Length: 267
Image (cartoon, rainbow, N blue to C red; front, side, top):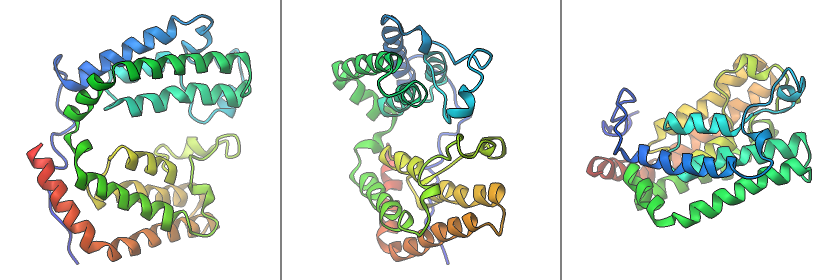
């Protein structure tokens, strides 16, 4: 057995720094600006900061992934968003949580939606400028091999992994409401939906990076459910089906990995 070698995929290291003219920074500015616009919208103050557990004692027991404009701004400053996609995904979480806790039609949810609508209008307004920044941050976004690679992986997830019997519990993030202590035991949650969203954003340039997330699903199940749990046996099968399929696509994937590596280097 052997694997493809590529030294440019893990470069530069995350030990790199913050330059003002850095593309990632410039983007953080446009995004933070949109945050100021949503915060300025009438009656949005409930979403400006995290829910106060002292006031709403059951909020963090019902909401799996909490989000607010303050936390959103913090993430932007830490340059956690390589593109508008990652940004919008976190933003809509505010709308989703309000729908879950207050109701799909609650006035609060409608208000949170107004922030999301404004965000989209802003994004579509700075369409081109945003496109160039995202491409400058990750040239691979416009690379056909990277796109072909992602497309194949996404099919491994939807065609093979999600097809495993009883696999549903691993299709989406564990819902805290039904498994109250899950996140107190699992500090590195992972699930098939999250992996698909990463694939959509071309996070993986090789099988290895893809498997680092795939493996977490089984590892987490072993940790929370136990080595002999029925849930772990299912997760084991999800991984096994993924591995088996990877060997079947070895020829195509190896070639794509080499091209992506070449494109990664040229970038």
